[PDB]
Amino acid sequence: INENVNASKSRIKDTDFAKETTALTKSQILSQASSSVLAQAKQAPNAALSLLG
Amino acid sequence: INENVNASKSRIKDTDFAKETTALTKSQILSQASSSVLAQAKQAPNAALSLLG
Image (cartoon, rainbow over all chains, first blue to last red):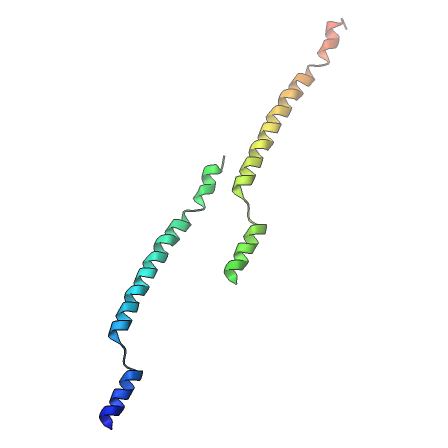
């Protein structure tokens, strides 16, 4: 019983390193994506300075 | 909500630099035009001095 119960807690609490590592990378990528696009946007207002006489 | 709200406040309170910069130019052009006409007008009465005085 101890074995099957230990097995059960694992299927509920234990982390699937494979799936989690995949997510950790996925998040890091989307983070880099946001960082770059944010920098692209932070420079957008500069456009005014140009059309500004 | 905050975003859409900031977006809305912009569509009403912020300045569309493009349109405004165009307007400032037109205003300046009209001003330089008016000044030119005005100077020609300031000398209009001089015509009398041609007919003696």
